Length: 117
Length: 8
Ligand SMILES: [Zn+2]
Ligand SMILES: [Zn+2]
Ligand SMILES: [Zn+2]
Ligand SMILES: [Zn+2]
Ligand SMILES: [Zn+2]
Ligand SMILES: [Zn+2]
Ligand SMILES: [Zn+2]
Ligand SMILES: [Zn+2]
Ligand SMILES: [Zn+2]
Image (cartoon, rainbow over all chains, first blue to last red; front, side, top):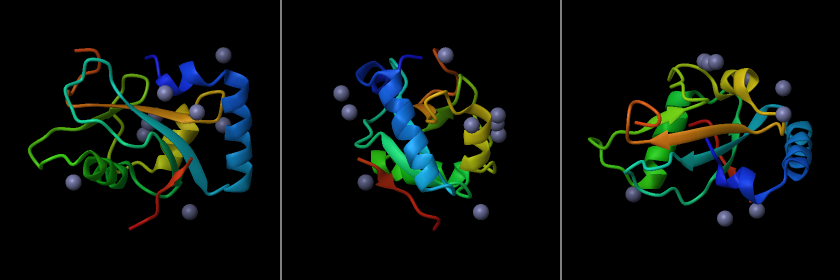
C-alpha cells in the first residue's frame, strides 16, 4: 500500500523522527493510520498517533471509530501488511512485529473485511 | 504533530 505520509516525507526524515520519538518515549510507539484506497468510509482527521505500548488493538479501534464518527453498524477494519490484527494484541506487540525501517507502524483502515476488495 | 493516545 502507498501511504501518503511516506510519499510526502523522504525515508531519512521519517527514520530520524521515528528513532527520536522511540528513544524519547520508550513505552510508546508511533503509528500512522490512513484510509485504504477505494474504501467507502469517513475520513480520519489525524494520521499520526503516539500510542502506549500496552494499549490493545481493540482499544485503538474504539478510539479511531469515534474519531471518524462511525455509527455502531458501520464496519471498521485495520490492516497491517494486508492482515487484520487481533483485538487482544497490544499495540506494542503489533509494532514490534511489523514496524517499518523508519520506526513507524503503518495501519490502513477500511469498511471492508478484506484489503483491496 | 502527534495525537497523544492514553490508556482508558
Ligand atoms: Zn498531505
Ligand atoms: Zn508533514
Ligand atoms: Zn507496560
Ligand atoms: Zn462523533
Ligand atoms: Zn498480533
Ligand atoms: Zn501480529
Ligand atoms: Zn524494531
Ligand atoms: Zn504479527
Ligand atoms: Zn528497505
